[PDB]
Amino acid sequence: DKNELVQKAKLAEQAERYDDMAACMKSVTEQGAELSNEERNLLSVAYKNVVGARRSAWRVVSSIEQKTAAAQQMAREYREKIETELRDICNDVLSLLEKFLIPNASQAESKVFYLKMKGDYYRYLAEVAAGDDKKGIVDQSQQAYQEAFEISAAAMQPTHPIRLGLALNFSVFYYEILNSPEKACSLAKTAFDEAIAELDTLSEESYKDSTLIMQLLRDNLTLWTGGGGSRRGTSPARMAGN
Amino acid sequence: DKNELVQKAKLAEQAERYDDMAACMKSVTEQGAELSNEERNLLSVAYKNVVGARRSAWRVVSSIEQAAAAQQMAREYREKIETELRDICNDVLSLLEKFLIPNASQAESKVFYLKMKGDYYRYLAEVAAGDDKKGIVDQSQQAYQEAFEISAAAMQPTHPIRLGLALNFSVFYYEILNSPEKACSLAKTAFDEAIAELDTLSEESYKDSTLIMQLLRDNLTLWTGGGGSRRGTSPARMAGN
Image (cartoon, rainbow over all chains, first blue to last red; front, side, top):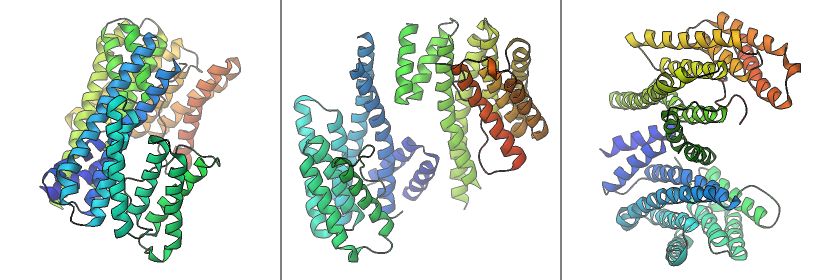
């Protein structure tokens, strides 16, 4: 039952049992009905955490590998184990998006959300890919983001958390996947300035959500222009509402 | 190979892959050789994190658990978490009974493992409710008492293991036995006996000891003075690398 799986997913989120949360939301998605905003946020949070554990572990192990021979081999083989899990996680999400979520999305908002998610999961694949395979992955990420960006540019107000979150993540893709920092800065700054210029369209209910992401844009711009900071930000999993 | 497993465990720790770390250290223990201090720390860290994820989730789900369908889902989720928690504790306790306690050739390692036995039965006592609770609590207390007597006879009051034992035994009295006076007494004595010999320590020994002495002091403050925060129990890595 759908309502039950959603309730179990919420409970799992509170317990920080993100594998359980992801299993619940994958089952919900596979029933083939369109997700509510709340259910999208549950799916997004679940997979962000499940993939994030591997992304974190990957950066640590990759760094250790580079720091150093038999030690270097162990670090390599452990990295590869983590990579296999990471690819499997990304493939699950991408399949859900291709098979169910994107083709059945009856609203532009949800379609943008999912096209952005497709860009994100291909981008996480691009973080670890090499050789002929990487080119294909990078092109998939870019195509998904570009389609999301065009739909959002005509459907959504500049203050819309999804539009902001997409701008943030697409900017990061330019910066670190394409190694295009000027383009990354231009995209982020444009999105920030358009939101400022159309603050009249930012509902009171959306203020907290939208301004959080405006802050992430600013902080990435501070980092990228030499004003300091920690690791660049990407979008929260829960961009708008509950 | 033991050296390889240990190197994999250290890598896992860096990655925060605690299931991997615990699998490595379980395999090491099962080869039947005594652990080094470093290996004990790896074992202890691995299982602290593996069980800890369940202890936190259990407290959240229990709290939420205070409509029929909703109540049942919460209960059944709690029970699933409890089953994982018991399975984790049973693995640890089995390793302790089969390999670590009977092979421990020094007082420090013997106390470390008897404390760990007390700890994992204590984690069982946090969730147990029925005929088996009495059994579980008695096992925790007996393991702690034996650790306490050995460490009182054989180890210096500044020893991070002796201090960590005092901390955890104090918490056992406070929250498992509902004996705050005794919990207080135990912690305060351990703190005071360590204060008297702090001048004797190296810089690195001072750091380790004072970290646990701070946890003792914080629990004493919390318990006598009041406060909302969660009491401290011992770090998994008490002394050294």
